[PDB]
Image (spheres, helix red, strand yellow):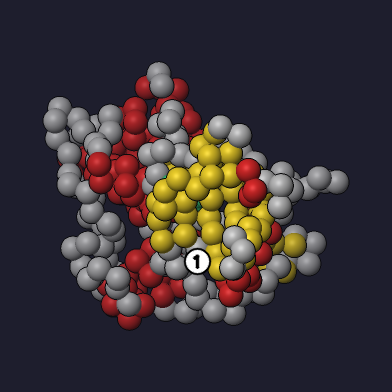
């Protein structure tokens, strides 16, 4: 179509399970283009569908531009064009850098604001359904030039129909990254007919992302090396069974160092992590509550 024909692909930046991401140039601006082959149409259409949700746009959700198709004369490519963020993922960003207390708050608060907006239902003519991500992880969050985050990779999301309490794709199977799966997802006790259960599972994964950020907070030169949650307990690419034995059976969570109690910002962050990590989903903090807590901390710090 008219958009893909005017875009020049410059570099393949990533190869995921669904599609390949490229840095492209559109009307002289950098854009990110996710390309799927003809046989991945279901995945491409679903992601285009979630990104076109009414009232979805928010400073902390990846800016979607357009879905399109491009025929090179041999095969057709299915495109999803979005805003380009040079830092890339929060995973890449935390591996490369350490952050200040201010930097940590900015990353955590923006992640929570994006999640609170996904989770929020807006009632009306131009109403927005509540949305649950189902695959929140530091590799699915991007860092913007201003040091704030935006949630990306919404292709596995589910949308709620509030009047009937029904989910748009009626999920009957476990999806997402095994390492970040909530205890109720790992042991398959989650009620997949209960939308609030998917919001609660996202909060647990956001808790693990906050732990990743806090390790990289550098105070008086003190900080931890980058690690994925459960790095000390499971192998790389862990199985459901491996995760379940740790999270559900032994009931372990990532370690919270006592030295996070000697700094106010880290203390608040530690308290949030613990309250995201309860085995009972109903006891977890909401994304709005986390946003309110970190907004108060940001104000106190003068960011
Ligand atoms: N869901 C979705 C759809 C289309 C592109 C993307 N990825 C990106 N978007 C914007 N900047 C980026 N920078 C670096 C790596 C990326 O992967 C990236 C995700």
Residue drawn at 78 percent across, 67 percent down: 164
Residue drawn at 75 percent across, 60 percent down: 162
Residue drawn at 66 percent across, 54 percent down: 67
Q: Position of residue 239 (x, y in %)?
A: 32, 77
Which one is nearer the viewer's eye here, 19 or 163? 19
Residue 286 in sight here: no
Q: Position of residue 4 (x, y in %)?
A: 63, 49
Q: Position of residue 119 (x, y in %)?
A: 61, 51
- Residue 122, compared with residue 77, is above or below; it is above
- Horizontal side, residue 236 vs residue 302: left or right: left
Q: Secondary structure at mark 1?
A: loop
Q: Which residue is mark 1?
A: 18
Which one is nearer the viewer's eye here, 223 or 45? 45
Which one is nearer the viewer's eye here, 180 or 72? 72
- Residue 73, compared with residue 245, is above or below; it is above
Mark 1, ligand 1, within 8 Å: the answer is: no
Circle 1 Cα neighbour tier, 10 Å, few/some/many (<14 / 14–19 / ≥20): some
Residue extending farthest left: 221
Residue 262 in sight here: yes
């Amino acid at each position: 179509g008219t958009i893909a024909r005017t875009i020049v692909l410059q570099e393949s930046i990533g190869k995921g399970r669904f599609g390949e991401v490229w840095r492209g140039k559109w009307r002289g601006e950098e854009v990110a283009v996710k390309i799927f082959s003809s046989r991945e149409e279901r995945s491409w259409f679903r992601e285009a569908e979630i990104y076109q949700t009414v009232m979805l746009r928010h400073e902390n959700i990846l800016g979607f531009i357009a879905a399109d198709n491009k025929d090179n004369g041999t095969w057709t490519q299915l495109w999803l064009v979005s805003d380009y963020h040079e830092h890339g993922s929060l995973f890449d960003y935390l591996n490369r850098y350490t952050v200040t207390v201010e930097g940590m708050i900015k990353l955590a608060l923006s992640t929570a604001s994006g999640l609170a907006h996904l989770h929020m239902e807006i009632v009306g003519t131009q109403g927005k359904p509540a949305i649950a991500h189902r695959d929140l992880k530091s590799k699915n969050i991007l860092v913007k030039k201003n040091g704030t985050c935006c949630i990306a990779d919404l292709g596995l999301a589910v949308r709620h129909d509030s009047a009937t309490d029904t989910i748009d794709i009626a999920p009957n199977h476990r999806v997402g990254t095994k390492r970040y799966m909530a205890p109720e997802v790992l042991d398959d006790s989650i009620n997949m007919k209960h939308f609030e259960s998917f919001k609660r599972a996202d909060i647990y994964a956001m808790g693990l992302v906050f732990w990743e950020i806090a390790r990289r907070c550098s105070i008086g030169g003190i900080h931890e090396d980058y690690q994925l949650p459960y790095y000390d307990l499971v192998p790389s690419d862990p199985s459901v069974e491996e995760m379940r034995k740790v999270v559900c059976e032994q009931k372990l969570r990532p370690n919270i160092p006592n030295r996070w109690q000697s700094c106010e910002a880290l203390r608040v962050m530690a308290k949030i992590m613990r309250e995201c990590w309860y085995a009972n989903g109903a006891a977890r903090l909401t994304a709005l509550r986390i946003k309110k807590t970190l907004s108060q901390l940001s104000q106190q710090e003068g960011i």
